[PDB]
Image (cartoon, coloured by chain):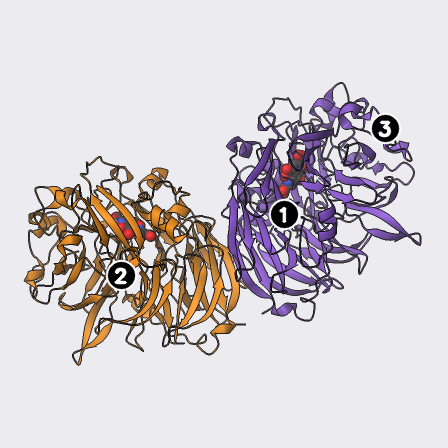
Chain colours: A purple, B orange
Amino acid sequence: NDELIKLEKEPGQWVMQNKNYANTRYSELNQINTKNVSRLRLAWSFSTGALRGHEGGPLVVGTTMYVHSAYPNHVYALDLTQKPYAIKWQYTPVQNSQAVAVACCDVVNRGLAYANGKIFMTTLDGQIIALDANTGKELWKMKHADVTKGETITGAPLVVKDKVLVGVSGGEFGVRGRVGAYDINTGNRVWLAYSQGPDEEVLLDSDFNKEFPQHGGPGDGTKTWPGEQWKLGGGTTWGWYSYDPALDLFYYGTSNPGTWNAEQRKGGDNKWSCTIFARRPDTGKARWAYQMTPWDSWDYDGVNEMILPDLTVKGKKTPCLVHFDRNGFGYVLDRRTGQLIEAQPFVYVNWAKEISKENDRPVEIPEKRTKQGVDTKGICPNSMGGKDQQPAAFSPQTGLFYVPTNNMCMNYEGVEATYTAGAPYVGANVLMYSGHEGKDDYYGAFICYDALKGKRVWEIHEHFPVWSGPVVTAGGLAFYGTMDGWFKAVDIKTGKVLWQQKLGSGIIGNPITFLGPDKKQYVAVYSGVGGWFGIAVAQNLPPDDPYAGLGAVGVAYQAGLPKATTVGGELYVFALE
Amino acid sequence: NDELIKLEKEPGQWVMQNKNYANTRYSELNQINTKNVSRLRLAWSFSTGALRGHEGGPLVVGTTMYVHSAYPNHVYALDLTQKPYAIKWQYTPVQNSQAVAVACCDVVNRGLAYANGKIFMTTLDGQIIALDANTGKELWKMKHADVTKGETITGAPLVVKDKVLVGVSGGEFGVRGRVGAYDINTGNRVWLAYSQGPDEEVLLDSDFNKEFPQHGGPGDGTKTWPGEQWKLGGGTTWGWYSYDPALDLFYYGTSNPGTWNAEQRKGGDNKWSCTIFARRPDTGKARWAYQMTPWDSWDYDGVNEMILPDLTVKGKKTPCLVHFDRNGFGYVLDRRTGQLIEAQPFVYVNWAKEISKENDRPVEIPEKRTKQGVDTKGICPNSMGGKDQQPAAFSPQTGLFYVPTNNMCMNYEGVEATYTAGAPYVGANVLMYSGHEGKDDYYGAFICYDALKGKRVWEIHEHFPVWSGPVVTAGGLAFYGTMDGWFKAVDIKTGKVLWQQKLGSGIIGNPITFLGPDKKQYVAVYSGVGGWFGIAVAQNLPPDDPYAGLGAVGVAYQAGLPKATTVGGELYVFALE
Ligand SMILES: O=C(O)c1cc(C(=O)O)c2c(n1)C(=O)C(=O)c1cc(C(=O)O)[nH]c1-2
Ligand SMILES: O=C(O)c1cc(C(=O)O)c2c(n1)C(=O)C(=O)c1cc(C(=O)O)[nH]c1-2
Ligand SMILES: [Ce+3]
Ligand SMILES: [Ce+3]
């Protein structure tokens, strides 16, 4: 989109969830820096009027801030010229409350998109809705997903050219993952790109994986599955999307291949679950695809963000894609072709020795691959991954990445799964605990990571998983939140905490930074705990069954989350003086 | 209670809702003052995990802060030694959710009491519950009110000696208002004092009103009503209680006399509705009582706080009771006898010329007394009163009062009412609007008032009603919140605002100030709009019928409250540094 390509360069605005199409989450603003951040204080706050998990973050376009909430997905426009703000408009969609019963991982929403004088939102119950950005008037609404089939929507849509790109959730409900493109003006569906099934549904361009046939090709959407198991094939698309306008490719990752009992998927790779896709936005046709975790047996969803830095590789400036996967590996690919440049662990990994440079496949440790009817113990990372959806940042100044991570392991036993449309299609008993096979007394870490060297530069051990995507700035600072409510600013060179404040609820939002109409720098973040690790608190679940929430309940209680935080939903905005 | 008499003198703690038994809401702390308050900033916050109206405030006892919420009435103990806090324990009572449907005026609760190692809470559904203050363990509980008869509890209980005093709500449901005294050590109900009915139920001491028999006497609880109309007689007890241990008297006010159609109560004063009671704590027996509004036709509940200052009256130090009634008059009584010393308007009043010096009865303006089947227009104040429950403060240094006020008027038409147990028993159509018979463009004011002179000293006009009870301090400051979310510090001498910050939701909490274990002064307040004026927002009500919420919906939309604030539930704590 030509407006967004222009606007995303402005230091004073924040026009899409991860700052720009490259998903760098980097701001050039330097009013707030390592010298003065100790003086940072709350400027103002705003209640979203919702409880449970508040993921994503606000947008700032012009002099208007756009705010979104957990279910029922209230949307607000705040006029920042009104000292400090006034509510310009609000919108709450009508939804089918049955959506709540088929949300796997809390009733979260990762946020709004802006383009062409319009705001775009997704709803838990499967709608994509366009609103007038200045009045809040509903312009069009479309049904993209079907709650009666166990589908929900939690991901933020992406506007590219005249299309709004919308995903789906339900990898634990046997859903056929896909991305739909809807016309920005009418909402009419233009194309629908599936993550499995026949080529006609997957949508492959004539040059698909041309340079890397070893990454797969035509027919693999069915041939790499037993029978018609692909019809329940997962590969959902609830993460963050990115875009390179020069290459005319947009990028995203896909979820686990449906049932968690790999026995019922045996015989093939189960493509294109756990896959990085690069597609043409006009047609949806794939130019390349790389499957990170063939025949997944761990729930290592591949949906984490696809950051698009230009890195110096073997002495030459190279258009890269960088992705910190649930499977614990930090991948660097050539974003033109899907060529694997590097893959090294960014957390402790014990299910695989390495990713092979020969065939780009994981070299598995067989004792850590799961199976039906027999437990597999001490798998690291757990299903929540080296990190979950919480997006990393990249600084072009340092050339390094700032990554929120999990530090947890699990036991995982496959169980026969039976499909009933609208009900869970899992087939696993999972127990979760702290990192390094339960030896660690902490469950998270915030790190600085060198993707090409495949090494951590520094690490901040955090008691709880870090479920907040940092913003990094030219002031030498990274901001992120903790699940017990601390909002922190750290020195990007050393990891030292330079400022912190305890807010009302665990933070699972991704902070932003922008300039107000007063030309002053502000830092804004949601508070309101939830998401998968926070499900025991958000859904008020008891400790009696530690297997509940597919392991999430036990581990949250072990880490002491329910004693550490209440539910909430508040936007906090900070500035100097 | 001897512990509370001792503790209430400590500058660093806040051991009951209005600071002390005299309900002065005054703190001797002066770390924060007129010279430095501009430097005040948020220190920390805590989400209550509930939405809708958050009335009252936290308690600070020792190094523990006790926090309460709107329905379902979560209770938390925060350990303030844990930099800045940790959740020490929490308790959520089991309730009958039918209570929500019979709450007149939002699902608020005015807060906790502390005494003798115990926390005492009330629940919307009619329970009084004693918890261990250090562990949160339930010690005892009793059913005090019955939701099937339209009873709820929203008021904060008061501990006096070895008794916890518990009121009831339901003046709009034909409830028989009463106060119960429960043994703090066992939960046994020791006595139960009704606001109407025969003397055996009202409970009168042998010297009742002996100095002022013109204020009423034996038998008036039935003889001042037509037939047995007293059986649906209201006089509920949902406001703030006060106590003078030197006099062995506790004090409180009573609600409207049930049906809003005065025609059905014609024939007498309807005692003891709209009444100030002084009762013996041992027996519940009344020593004196003064009815402010005989034969009410306006819903002028008498429940507002009974502040117990010692004032110089005609040169003599006098133990006074000062009360800013819903009816718009600022009453000063001798708290030994119920002598009426002074009564003058603290807001614009047009329903009465004055209170008679001859017999202490309002001199009514007949045109403004409401009637059955005919509309009466331009009545000031409206039923929300000169002020509602939001409690005023008194400074012993200045000898003046700092009062949050409403600036609103109404039309009110009596309608014949039919009693159905558990259903509303109102009988009125009420249209509300701004002050001075709808001429004004603002709906509230924060004032400094001289009670003996009967004069405002200064006034700050506020766009919304001021539904927040100030804390006033020896630093020369008054702190209060507005319904569009501004928390403000004013210079008590000039009435100038010296500091303000916009928070996430309208403030209907009453702020407190205390010393942390770090010896630093903090100011704390709930944010989370609701209560009667906020009902359109708290209950998500449309503007279609302006008469809805007994007039509250119309006036809240006219004032623009739904455009100004969202719902919430957050405790904000401020300090210097
Ligand atoms: O397979 C799926 O469709 C799907 C959807 C979602 C979601 O929509 O939030 C999550 C996951 N999987 C998942 O595996 C997981 O780790 C997870 C965490 C969260 C969260 O917001 O905290 N959502 C999801
Ligand atoms: O007569 C009653 O029993 C009763 C109860 C309550 C309550 O319990 O909150 C209010 C009132 N009346 C009332 O008249 C009124 O002005 C009012 C305002 C509020 C509030 O919290 O904002 N409660 C009540
Ligand atoms: Ce999944
Ligand atoms: Ce009332």
Residue linked to disc 2 = B305
Q: Is residue B210 above or below residue A216?
A: below
Quarter holding the C terminus of chain A? bottom right
Q: Is B163 displayed left or right of B444 in the figure?
A: left
Give percent across and percent down for residue B19: 34, 66
Neighbourhood count class around disc 1 (C-alpha, 10 Å): few under 14, some 14–19, many 20 upward: many
Q: Mark 2 touching mark 1, by CB under 8 A?
A: no
Extreme residue in the bottom direction: B315
Location of ligand 1 given as a quarter of the image: top right
Residue linked to disc 3 = A217
**For residue A305, which numbered disc appears in the image?**
none
Q: Earlier in the sequence, mark 1 or mark 3?
A: 1
* Amino acid tagged 2: Glu
Quarter of the rendering containing residue A141? top right
Q: Answer yes or no: is residue B338 visible.
A: yes
Neighbourhood count class around disc 2 (C-alpha, 10 Å): few under 14, some 14–19, many 20 upward: many
Q: Is B559 displayed left or right of A172 in the figure?
A: left
* Amino acid tagged 1: Gly
Could you say whether the residue bearing mark 3 is in a helix, strand or loop? loop
Quarter holding the N terminus of chain A? top right
**Residue at x-position 81% and y-position 57%:** A399
Distance between mark 1 and mark 3 Cα atoms: 34 Å
